[PDB]
Length: 99
Image (cartoon, rainbow, N blue to C red; front, side):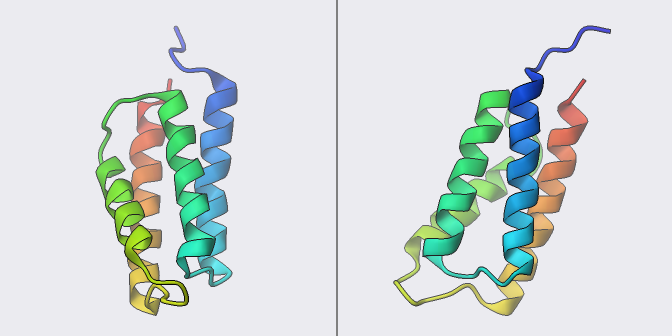
C-alpha cells in the first residue's frame, strides 16, 4: 500500500513520545524540565500530520498547564500519572493514524 507520512518524521515523533514518558518516570516534574520536552514533542507530531487525532488536544492542555507553573513549582505525583496516561493514549491514537 501507499504510505502517506514521512518515516523520518515519524521516527522522531515516536522517539519524542518515549523520551517524555521516560523523563516522567525519572521524576522530571518541573516546568523547566517538562516544557522543552512537551514542546519538541508537539513540533515533531505536527511535522508528521496536522490532523487533530484523538487525545492530541490533551497534550496542548498539559503544555498550557505546565507553562503556568512558577519556577520551583512542580507537577504533583498524581498529575504526573495523569500526564503519563494521556501521553500513552495520544501515542496510541497517533500510531493508529500511521500507514
